[PDB]
Amino acid sequence: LTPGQRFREAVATEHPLQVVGTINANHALLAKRAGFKAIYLSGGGVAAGSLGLPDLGISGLDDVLTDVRRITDVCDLPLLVDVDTGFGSSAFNVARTVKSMIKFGAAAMHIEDQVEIVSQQEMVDRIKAAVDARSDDSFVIMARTDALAVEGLQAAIDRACACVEAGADMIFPEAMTELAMYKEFAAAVKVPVLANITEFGATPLFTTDELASADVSLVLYPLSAFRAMNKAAENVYTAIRRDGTQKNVIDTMQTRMELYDRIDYHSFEQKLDALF
Amino acid sequence: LTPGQRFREAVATEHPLQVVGTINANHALLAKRAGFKAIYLSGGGVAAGSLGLPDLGISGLDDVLTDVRRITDVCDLPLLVDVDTGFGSSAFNVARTVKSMIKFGAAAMHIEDQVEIVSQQEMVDRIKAAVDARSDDSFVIMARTDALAVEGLQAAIDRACACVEAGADMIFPEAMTELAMYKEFAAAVKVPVLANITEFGATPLFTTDELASADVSLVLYPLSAFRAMNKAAENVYTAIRRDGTQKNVIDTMQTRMELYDRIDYHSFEQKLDALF
Amino acid sequence: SLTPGQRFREAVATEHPLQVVGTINANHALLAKRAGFKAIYLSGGGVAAGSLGLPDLGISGLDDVLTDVRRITDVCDLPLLVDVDTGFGSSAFNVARTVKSMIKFGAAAMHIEDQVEIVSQQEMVDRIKAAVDARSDDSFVIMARTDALAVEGLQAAIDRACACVEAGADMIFPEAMTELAMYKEFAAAVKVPVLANITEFGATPLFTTDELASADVSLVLYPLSAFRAMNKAAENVYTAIRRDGTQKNVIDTMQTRMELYDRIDYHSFEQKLDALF
Amino acid sequence: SLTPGQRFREAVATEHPLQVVGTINANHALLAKRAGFKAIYLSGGGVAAGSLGLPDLGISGLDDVLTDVRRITDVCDLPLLVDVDTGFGSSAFNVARTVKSMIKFGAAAMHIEDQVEIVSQQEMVDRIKAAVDARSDDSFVIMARTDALAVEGLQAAIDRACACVEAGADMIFPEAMTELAMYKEFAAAVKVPVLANITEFGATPLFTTDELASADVSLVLYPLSAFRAMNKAAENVYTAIRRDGTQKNVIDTMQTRMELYDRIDYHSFEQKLDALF
């Protein structure tokens, strides 16, 4: 199966499909072990995690592709990737973004209508450029829109329907925080709708049964693991500096034997034995 | 000050100098906020964290330099980098490693005598190659040796002294589990000695006071933060998969407002206002 | 819809012998396609000497080669045969990472050699086994390169090649074969496609496609030919500009702006924008 | 111990006008150094057309340019002037990452232009400020490139360039200037070093270093000259190989193996091994 076919199958056999943010290759394998069928590379996470920078469009296609290659080299779970507005203003930038994502093994990407949003026709043109560049039809193009917040619910439906007509496979409406609105949105746009359930934001922490009842097809936890990983890491640095040892924070650590297990150290031994 | 100058000064103004592993640029900034004067890029961390791979020499110079550039682009703490045996068998491979580490902003590297170890003359020739390629004399070349485990303490002192005569600035003896052995090693070798205080290994979790009494000049916590980060992330994946929400692991998460503070989001707005 | 390896196998099946030309960069891959070639090559000595300005002494790594592979295959659909030295590391895992990366970054084929003086037939077979096992797309071609002829003689080179074929090598690249009759004996014995490396200024005669076909050779490689001419031409420009204080005396040696626009298909970009918008 | 930027400023101070030659790759950087040039150039059109096989339509990005900067500056110590188009993104932060990345990867200087038609004088001044503020090494040269002459006329060009200088621009690259008398007037008004772009097959005449010295021009750029000769030579080889079934008829166009070993100083690697061991 192509990465994109895997993503489509995940969406078809889980309702709603849970998609978790994976900050690096290691966390992709943890996500697979935990039983998730799809994973996500947050653009905010590439910026804040990989580059230690704010999510202010400093991160480029190269930064994101590095993380895609590292994750898809070891993890076979379909990866949804945040590509912002396509990494440049031209249809040719959007095409290079699409073709590079497919080549480096990403299963899906979401592209947004940020410039404030562009006009419905500019967003349709962005989607047409991505659909036209696609060398593998199974690769999923998800249209992300901030139209609800800027122009209202009917504006967001009309824009999403125009994106679907242009070839968008799935819709990511931003700032949608009422289950009734998700349900009305899903009935109108017909294709799979993603609910972004991030923490410390506008949205209620809706559950999978709640989202399924509102006919939502995917639910995204874009930075959840990362936020816990930073608190845990900061506790270790503070403890080492204060105590002059890590001994008082040993209880918060993955063991050496857990790590060997989670990167499948044994399968490497097994490979050499089978070969020689 | 060159990164190398900062590393030398850190060792001169802290006894022993605490050097913490930083798996990514984000955690480099966390370590700086916690008050550490020096940080580390573990080669086992690039493998296990960045590539999701065992530490079996699959990770190469390019994988490591990508992590070096990401960290030194945003964090000004001197970075000590694990370069295995120099990423190739030639003096020219060791030379390209050295020059690339200096160019991409690393302050120090450690290079080891792994092939079982190489002859004392082979290790000396590796040090000479690295020392000859150094375009900036302040960049620290740290000789790492498994000679105590293979040939006993007197061999380990002889080899280390031979590395210092070849131009090695500092010494990283592997698997030293008695403060008395450190104390003796330090007086015999004369140059700064690093103690590798990793978890779940042979070494006791010695304190800064203990190591200062044994004349140890640097103490390394290579993966401490990483191991806590992975347990925290696995907890979040488990909870989300079990509960159909992240509701029950919110209390383990760095807040949005903390993330913004730790990647200094507000100095970006400040530069904008200060510039235009 | 063919994979790069299917394109490579199909080129070998439809041209006898198949001319494979070294392409130092994406621009020259496009020149080779326009000249009518069905396959191109990424020389390791060309990554070293051209892309890095370095001698071919194993300083160039997987990352360096992959960058050129990605630049070429992103714009040129011709199957790319790639020199991967000994696999960029001593471990079966290094060989596996090289094979998977070459497939992912769009190479059609790779050649891996028995250089450490050669390693034992067992070690070379182990290298091929590691490469064949790592292959995620069976259509990707693994070519075994061997210097056994010069080190151990013809029968040794034949035995090593057949062992490589038994380990799953698809095609064989013998080094230092200087006699046409030796290629014919070697091709009859090993059975799979044989590549003749017709580089310049080396031991090999400049054998023609007719001569190689008569010796049953399946591929003929011109690994650095365009690069060599490209460097003389460029040096003649630098010299002329430094000496004369102008490029006047080298204008006639240049590709025109209109030729370059044609060779990179500039106007097919404007047509795409019209087609779509 | 000179920084790249200091070497560039030293080259401009010691040669009038300073010849700056385009170098498509690290190999050609070493040829330019052998020919006696004191400064070299990474064309953004050359990264697109040569490294990527693409037209110069803003598809090439910071990563593509940095790879070529690193490859060249790793082996060639001549100061490299880099085309960074409009800074690779519309934010002052994009401009800042471009400046810091170019300094870290070993570039001596960059030109950044007022393309969006051009932006307003204030928006170009804001580009230069963003770049000047981001500079961690003040020896690194910021060159303002402007198409104001063609769009708004010479006085507009001078005022824009003077406002770029007040914002901290070290040097000026005026686009589409084709009269020696105009270079002289422009140079007199702006005061800082002015670069003449003497590309081929364009609107500019092939002005010589003496003519440009007489018009007070401080730098002369030959941005793609060597690349254009390299492409014609490489196409001649491909054409000959396809037509003849052999390279025999184009051997005389080729750099020899002995010349290639000389130009990448193969000897100095053997000498280094001897010295160390």
Image: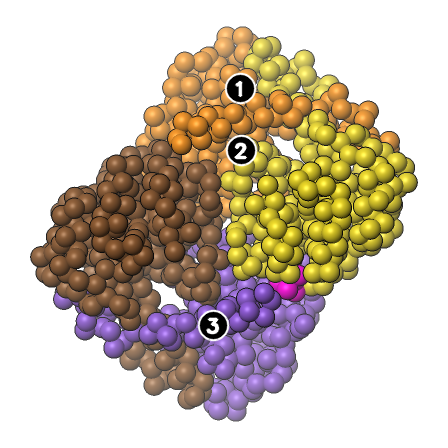
Chain colours: A yellow, B orange, C purple, D brown
Residue C8 in view? yes
Number of residues whose C-alpha sits closer than 10 Å to that of mark 1, classed few (under 14), some (14–19) or many (20 or more): few
Check the picture and name the quadrant holding the N terminus of chain B.
top left
Say which residue appears at 35% left-offset and 71% top-offset.
C257
Measured Cα–Cα span from mark 3 to mark 1: 53 Å
User: Label for residue C267?
Assistant: 3
Circle 1 or circle 2, nearest the eye: 2
Region rendered in magenta = A131-135
Measured Cα–Cα span from mark 3 to mark 2: 39 Å
Question: Would you place residue C75 above or below residue A210 in this image?
Answer: below
Residue C85 placement, left or right of D168: right
Label 1 sits on residue: B33
Residue A133 lies in the magenta-colored region: yes
Residue at disc 2, secondary structure: loop
The spot of residue A53 in percent (x, y) is 53, 33
Check the picture and name the quadrant holding the C terminus of chain B.
top left
Residue at disc 3, secondary structure: helix
Label 2 sits on residue: A53
Number of residues whose C-alpha sits closer than 10 Å to that of mark 3, classed few (under 14), some (14–19) or many (20 or more): few
Circle 3 or circle 1, nearest the eye: 3
Number of residues whose C-alpha sits closer than 10 Å to that of mark 2, classed few (under 14), some (14–19) or many (20 or more): many
